[PDB]
Every structure is written in structure tokens, then in C-alpha cells.
Amino acid sequence: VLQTIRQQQSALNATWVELLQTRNTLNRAGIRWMMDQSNIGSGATVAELMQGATNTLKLTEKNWEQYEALPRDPRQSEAAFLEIKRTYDIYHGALAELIQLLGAGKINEFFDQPTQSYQDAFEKQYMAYMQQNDRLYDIA
Amino acid sequence: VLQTIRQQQSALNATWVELLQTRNTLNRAGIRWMMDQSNIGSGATVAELMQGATNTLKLTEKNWEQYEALPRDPRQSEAAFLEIKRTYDIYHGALAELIQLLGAGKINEFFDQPTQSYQDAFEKQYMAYMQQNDRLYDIA
Ligand SMILES: [Cl-]
Ligand SMILES: [Cl-]
Ligand SMILES: [Cl-]
Ligand SMILES: [Cl-]
Ligand SMILES: [K+]
Ligand code: NA
Ligand code: NA
Ligand code: NA
Ligand code: NA
Ligand code: NA
Ligand code: NA
């Protein structure tokens, strides 16, 4: 009912969060990488931070696949779902690419990547779709 | 009453989400800082990143005061809210400290701060608060 959508919402939202956690951890690995170049390294290591971001990006893919396999109400928009998946797939792909640039030490390319646009296109769709699902609440 | 929950959950989630975008932005700024100091600055500027971070930390403050003023059902746990507040206030205050540290060139104190621990601690209370509200939705 209003619970099949509250449950589909929560799945999607754990994808959002894990993407945002992957992104931040990766940007931590960036600082440490830069410090190591200036031999002022300290705290968490590049290798450990990359490990957590490999972790949370895999968690991201698994949270996504669970949100897809959830059922959809017919009253929900199929173009919406497909636009959610288009932006996710760019965003996740972008974070998967950050993992490679850093391992290869491509700090500028790493940092010049417009992850922020990819994320914003995905956040745009997320916010729309939660409005369309909150409406389904208002009317049930 | 069921509507008053989703409203709470959405206000609190919006704070979470924004606490995470701020952390990522801050870490972006430290990479760029490090880069400026090594004369390989590219991408977005420290100044642009620090003003996004300043901006999103106020949105978090605001998102938070909106969640707080939403009426809390009597079946919801006053200790649970109090513990969210505790971990929220540590986490928020910590990202505020990161703004001051980076402004001051204090990159090691920036990178060393145990932000993860404050985030984890907030996320623990948030995950538990949701499962409770979700069991509570279930009942009704
Ligand atoms: Cl590069
Ligand atoms: Cl961008
Ligand atoms: Cl320092
Ligand atoms: Cl920590
Ligand atoms: K991890
Ligand atoms: Na943006
Ligand atoms: Na929300
Ligand atoms: Na600098
Ligand atoms: Na910029
Ligand atoms: Na603002
Ligand atoms: Na407090």
C-alpha cells in the first residue's frame, strides 16, 4: 500500500546515502594522497580510505539493485523510474571512475571530474520522485 | 499521526543528507588547498568550495530546526530524540570546526579530526530512530 512505496523510497534513499558516503571517503583519500606527496601524511591512509570506498560503492550497487527489484505501483511514473536510473548509472559510474584515477595517481583528473553535476542530476530526479510519492500518500 | 511521522522522517533525512554533502565539500576544499600549496591547482577553488560548505551547513542547521519543531508523537522516545540531538550537535559543530581549521591553513588538524566517529555516532541514532518509526507505521 503506502508501505510498498515507503519501502521503495527507503531503498532508494539508502542508495543516495551510500553514494554520498562513497563520494566523501574518496575525497578523503584525495587529501591523504596529496599529503603523502608532501610527506606530511597522517591519520587514515590512502589504501584504507580506498578500501572503504570500494566497500561503500559495492554497498551502493547492492542498495540500488534492491530498490529496482522492489515492486512499483501502477500509478507511479515509468519515465520517472527510468530517469532515476539514468542519472544513478552516470553517478555511480563516475564514482567507480574516481577509484581508478586515484589508484593511478591522477589527482588533477580526479579532482577536475564534474562529479557534482552527475550528483545534482541524480538529486534532481530523487527529489521529484519523492514528491510524486508523497502525493500518492496525500491521496491514499 | 502517520502523516506526522513521514514528515519527521523526511525532515531528519534531509539533515543527514546535507551533513554528508557538507563533509564532502569540505574534503574537496582540502584537496584544492593542498593543491594550491603544491602549485597544481585546478578544478573548483578553495573559496568556491568553502562558500558552498558554509551555505550547506546553514541549510543543515535549518533542516534540523525544522525537524525539531515538528510535533513528536507521545509514543516516540524522548530519550531517542535527545540522543539524536546529542550526536547531531557534535557532528554539526565538528564540520563548523573544519571550516575554521581550513581557513587557518591547519591542514593536519583538519585531516586528523575524528569526523567519521561523529558521523558514525549520528548515523547509529538515525538508523535506530527510523526502524522504530517504521515499526510504528507498521502498527497503524
Ligand atoms: Cl591528473
Ligand atoms: Cl560540476
Ligand atoms: Cl595543521
Ligand atoms: Cl574517526
Ligand atoms: K567502509
Ligand atoms: Na550543484
Ligand atoms: Na527528506
Ligand atoms: Na593553501
Ligand atoms: Na566551483
Ligand atoms: Na545557506
Ligand atoms: Na547536544
Image (tube, coloured by chain):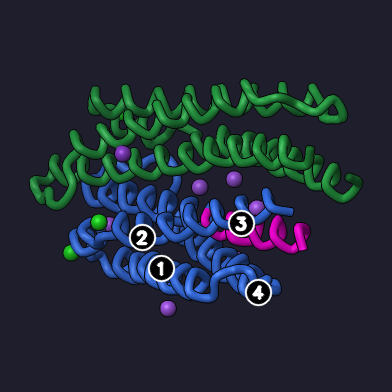
Chain colours: A green, B blue
- State whether label 2 is within 8 Å of ligand 4: no
Where is mark 3, residue-wise? B133
Q: Do callouts 3 and 2 point to residues on the same chain?
A: yes
Please state which of residues B134 and A56 is positioned toward the viewer in this rendering.
B134
Number of residues whose C-alpha sits closer than 10 Å to that of mark 2, classed few (under 14), some (14–19) or many (20 or more):
some
Q: Is label 2 in a helix, a strand or a loop?
A: helix
Residue B23 spot, x, y in % from top left: 41, 54
Marks 3 and 2 in Cβ contact (< 8 Å) = no
Q: Where is residue B21 in the image (x, y as percent from the top left)?
A: 49, 51
Q: Image point 69% across, 60% down: which residue?
A: B5
Looking at the rendered structure, the number of numbered marks drawn on it comes to 4
Q: Which amino acid does label 3 sit on?
A: Asn
Proximity of marks 1 and 3: CB atoms separated by less than 8 Å:
no
**Residue span colored magenta:** B1-16
Residue at the disc numbered 1: B87
Q: Which chain carries label 4?
A: B
> Could you give the CA–CA distance between mark 2 and mark 1, rounded to whole angstroms?
6 Å
Amino acid under disc 4: Pro
Residue B72 vs residue B114: left or right?
right
Disc 2 designates what residue?
B121
Q: Quadrant of residue A76?
A: top right
Of the numbered discs 4 and 2, the one sitting upstream in the chain is 4
Q: Nearer the viewer, mark 3 or mark 2?
A: 3
Q: How far apart are marks 1 and 3 (CA)?
A: 19 Å
Q: Quadrant of residue B132?
A: bottom right
Evaluate if marks 2 and 1 touch, with contact meaning CB atoms under 8 Å apart: yes
- Asked if disc 4 and disc 2 are in contact, CB closer than 8 Å, the reply is no
Measured Cα–Cα span from mark 4 to mark 2: 25 Å
